[PDB]
Image 1 (cartoon, helix red, strand yellow):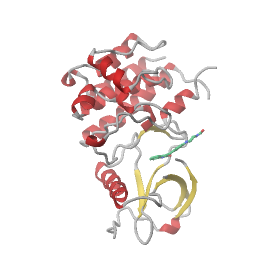
Image 2 (cartoon, rainbow, N blue to C red):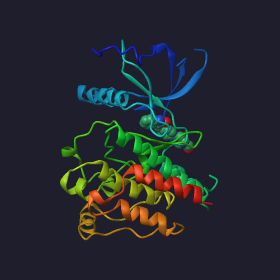
Image 3 (cartoon, rainbow, N blue to C red):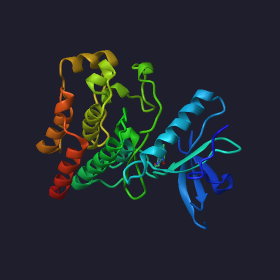
Image 4 (tube, protein in one colour):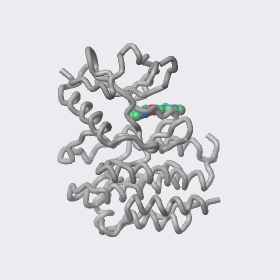
Amino acid sequence: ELPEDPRWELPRDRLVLGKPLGQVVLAEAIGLPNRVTKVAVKMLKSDATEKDLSDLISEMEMMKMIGKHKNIINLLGACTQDGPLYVIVEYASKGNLREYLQARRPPEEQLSSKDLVSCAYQVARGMEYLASKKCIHRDLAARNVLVTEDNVMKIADFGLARDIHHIDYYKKTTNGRLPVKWMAPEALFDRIYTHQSDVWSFGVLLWEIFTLGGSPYPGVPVEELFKLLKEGHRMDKPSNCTNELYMMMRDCWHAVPSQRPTFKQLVEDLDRIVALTS
Ligand SMILES: O=CN1CCN(c2ccc(CC3C(=O)Nc4ccccc43)cc2)CC1
């Protein structure tokens, strides 16, 4: 039923399926001839519907068009014939950025100020490329940024299929958080997603980096959040964060979308700051 694509197809016998990472499983690919590469494999569950298959195929086709970049999860290959569709993607051995940051908080080794600003820069870089490829993430957060064994930040879930007119606002993440806390007011209230709302989300992501896994608006429910946003509320400056970096966050949270900086700008700024960061 699935169309063959010689550009990305890998024989099934080349993919040794391993431990589930979260369905996404860790695996080893032989070749990609006599070397094995640890990869992540995305697949469907038994109780899945043809819709679920549709979405999975959509995410793969999306990854194909977007192309490669050091700071995004890249497509490595796929097993589409004679069996369950397997979408082989890059493996991130250190999990998501939130956890990575939390697991290094002082009472695993602590991160330096330069390390933190460097984390931000790489994320801005992944986004700059995605934006240039005409892609709107719609859910940029530290939970959706993965860290490789080499500490390379990689943006994930950028090719995901989603119905904005079907988003349950009263739904928590696996860790029990409310995704609406990363959405720009225009995206949340007017359902208007742009590279600019992604910038708003980047400001929230920056805040998580400088709070080392901090939760945005603890104890604040959907209804109260709407009110904060309507009143033009902005979170406080994280301790151990320069005024310069807080200003960046504040700039990303500009009420007017057109006045927010672009990822191209952010990349220039962060590139300059990193070098000035001890
Ligand atoms: O305590 C240590 N660890 C570190 C690794 N981690 C972890 C958990 C999940 C994943 C998933 C994962 C991945 O590695 N690549 C990729 C691409 C798309 C979607 C999901 C993924 C990758 C690593 C779990 C916890």
